[PDB]
Image (tube, coloured by chain):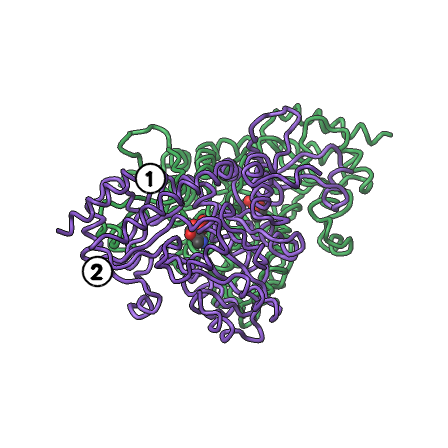
Chain colours: A purple, B green
Amino acid sequence: DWADRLRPETIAIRAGIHRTQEQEHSEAIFPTSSFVFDSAEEAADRFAGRVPGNIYARFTNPTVRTFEERLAALEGAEACVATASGMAACLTAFMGILKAGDHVVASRSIFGTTVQLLGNILSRFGVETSFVPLADVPAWRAALRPNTRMLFLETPSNPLTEIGDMQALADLAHVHDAWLVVDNCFCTPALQQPLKFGADLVIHSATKYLDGQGRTLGGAVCGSTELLNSGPRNFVRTAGPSLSPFNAWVQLKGLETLGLRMERHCANAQKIAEWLEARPEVARVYYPGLDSHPQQALAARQQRLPGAILSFDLHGGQKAAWAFVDALRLLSLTANLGDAKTTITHPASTTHSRVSPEARAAAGVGDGLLRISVGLEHADDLREDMERGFAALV
Amino acid sequence: DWADRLRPETIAIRAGIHRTQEQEHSEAIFPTSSFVFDSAEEAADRFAGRVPGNIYARFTNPTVRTFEERLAALEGAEACVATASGMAACLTAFMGILKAGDHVVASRSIFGTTVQLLGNILSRFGVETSFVPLADVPAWRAALRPNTRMLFLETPSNPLTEIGDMQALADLAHVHDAWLVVDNCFCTPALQQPLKFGADLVIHSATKYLDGQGRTLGGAVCGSTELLNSGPRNFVRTAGPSLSPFNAWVQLKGLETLGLRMERHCANAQKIAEWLEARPEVARVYYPGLDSHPQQALAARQQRLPGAILSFDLHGGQKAAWAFVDALRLLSLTANLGDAKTTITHPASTTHSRVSPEARAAAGVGDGLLRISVGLEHADDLREDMERGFAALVA
C-alpha cells in the first residue's frame, strides 16, 4: 500500500522494523542461539515449514532480519542475507551459486582478498577464474567460456576509481546464461543500485560505509527471493558464516544515516580532489567527479554522486609518498575505507605489495600513488593536514 | 616458566590476557575493523610480515585472540582460530584442509547440519563423503578410499551418546595419510581433550557450552601451529567467517566458569539419567555414565565426566513423547544444548525430521525418543517437571 512510495532516506530509518509486544521504539538486540516452541506440535510444524517462525539463530535472528530487510529495501532488492564479513558475502555468492567445473570472469582490480579467495582457495575446489580490465567490455567478452557462470566486479574500482559498464556486462552475462555480481562497497545503495542495471546479486561489506564508523565486520548478499533461495541462503545457514546480532544492530543503525553521511563524504571528496589536481607536486588525481576522469560520464550515469574515495600520483614516487604521509597529523594511516575518520594508505607497499611491478604497471598502481578515503571532518582541517605532507617534500 | 604448571581452572581464568596500558582488570572489547600505523615504513613492514602487529580485524583482533589462546590452552593445543559459528568451524576444517578430489569418512550421527555441509555443499565442490556407524571401527576401515584425507566424528554422539574410539581412529587415519578431526561440543575441553588420543584438529561450537548460556554463535578450530598454518587460518582470513569481538568477549568470559558449570551439568545429568531408567514409562536411557551404556568404559577412558546430554525412549511412540513434553512447564522446548536452561526436544519430528523414518530406525533414533540437555537448575525441580510429563501419560 502506502509504504511502496517512500524515499530512500525514510526507508533507511523505518524499514525492517517488527516491534515486539514491548513496543520498543528502537530496534532490539536478540542475543539468542535458539528459540522456544509452545508445544511439540508447534516445533514439528516449524521444523516442517508448515508455519513460519524462528528455530535457530544461524537460520533466523530478528536483529539480523531487520538489517537484511532494511538493506535490501535500500538496494531495491527483494531479499537479502547477511554474513559475518564482506569476504563471507563474496564466499556466499561464489559457493552458493557456483560448483566445481564452473568458470568466473572477474575484474582484475577487485579487493585483493577477493582475488585470493577466487584464485588461491576456490581454484582448489574446481572453480576457474579469468581476470580482465574493468572498463574493457571486449576483454570481458573475449574471456567468456562455455562454463562461465558468473561475472564479478566492483565499480568504482580500487584504488583508481575506474568504472564498469554494468548494463553492458549484465547483457553480456545474461546472453551467455551467466549471472552478474556487483560488489557495491564503493558507492553503497545511497549512491548506486546495481540491480537497476541488470545485476543479479549485489555484495556488500557492511564493514565499510553501512557501519560508516569502523566498528564492526559484516557483509550481505542482495537479490531476488528466487535467486537467494537457490543456494546462497542455504549456504549461510549450513556453512554458518553468520552475522552476530550485535554487529547487525550496529550496522542497521548505521544505515539510518547513510544518505546524509555519503553526501558529506562526497562533498569533501570533490573539494579535495580538485584542490589536489592543481598542486604542482601531484601528477594526476583519480576521482570520478573530475573532468579528467576518462569515464566521468559512465560514472554519472550509474551513480547519484561520484563517491568519496580518491587516489593521486605525486612526483617523486615512493620516497615522496612516504614522506608525505609521515608528516600527516590528522589523517589515519590505515588500510581501510568507509569511516568518518579520513584514511590514507600507500597501496604499492601495503595492499598491492605482493603484486608484481608489471601487473601494478598494467593496472596503473604506481609507486607514487596514495589512496585517500575521505571522511567527514572539516575539509579545511583535511586540507591543512595535507599541506603538511606537501611541505615535507621541500 | 611458572605458568606451565597451572591447572585448567586457573588457565580458563587467566590465559590469553594481554592488558593494555590502561591496566584494565577485565578483558576489553575491541570493536574495530582496522589498525593505525605510526609511519609509512611500519605499514609496509607489517604488510610484509617483517614485524608483529595488527593489520585488519578479519585476521587479528585482540578480543578474538584472547578467546583463541584461552580455548587452545584448555585443549592443550598450540593454536586456535575462531569462526563465526560451529558450522563455520566445520567449514574451515574441511576447506582449509581438503581440496577437490579428496574423500571424507564421517560418523553417520554427526550434527545434521554438518551432514548437509559435507553431503550437499562440499559435494558440489569435488569433496566425496562416506558415512559409517560411530562405534564400528571395521566399518570405518572398509569405507577408506585411496583419496581419503580426513576422518570426521563427534564423541559422545547425539542423540544416543554413542562413543568413538578416538585413538583407534587416529591410528587408522594416520596409517592412511589422513587427518582425524573431532567435534568436541558434547564434552568441551573441561571433560575431553581429543589431542591426547591422536586427533589432528578439534572443532568447537562456542554456541553451546563455552558460552554456556544461549547468548551467541561462535566456533573454533584447535590444532598444531603447523597444521592451522597450512590453510585453516588463511581460509578464515580470506573467506572471512570471522568471529565478532562482542561474541568472542561473551565466550572468553564463559570459558572462565566452564569447569564449574560442566561439573554441575554432569552431576545433574547422572541423577536424572538413573531416575529415568527406573521409571516404568521409560524403555531405555542413553547416557555414558550409566552402567547399561554399552561403552561406559571407553567413555570413562576418554572423558573426565560422562557429559550432560541424555536421551530416553518412552514406551509408546510420538504420541507419548508429545504428551510428555506438552505437560512440561519448566524445561525449554527448543532444539539446542549447552545452556544453563535445561532443554528438551523430540528428534524424530525436529532435528532428524528430514531423515527418512527407515534411516532413523537404522540409526536407532525412534519415534519415542526424547533428548534432554541437562542444565544447571536444581535437579529436584527438573525431576518434578518431568513427573508432570509422566503424569500426562495417564490420559
Rendered position, A97 above or below A383: below
The residue beneath circle 1 is B5
Secondary element type, mark 2: helix
Quadrant in which residue B139 is drawn: bottom right
The residue beneath circle 2 is A317
Res B297 visible: no
Residue pictured at 74% horizontal, 27% vertical: B387
Secondary element type, mark 1: helix
- Pinpoint residue B259: horizontal percent, then vertical percent: 48, 34
Kind of residue at badge 2: Gly
Kind of residue at badge 1: Arg
Q: Are marks 2 and 1 in contact (CB under 8 Å)?
A: no
Q: Residues within 10 Å of mark 1 (few under 14, many from 20)?
A: few
Q: Chain of mark 2?
A: A
Left/right placement of residue A57 relative to residue A355 reads right
The mark tally for this picture is: 2
Quadrant in which residue B120 is drawn: bottom right
The residue furthest left is: A394
- Pinpoint residue B269: horizontal percent, then vertical percent: 62, 34
Of tags 2 and 1, the one toward the viewer is 2
The residue furthest right is: B395
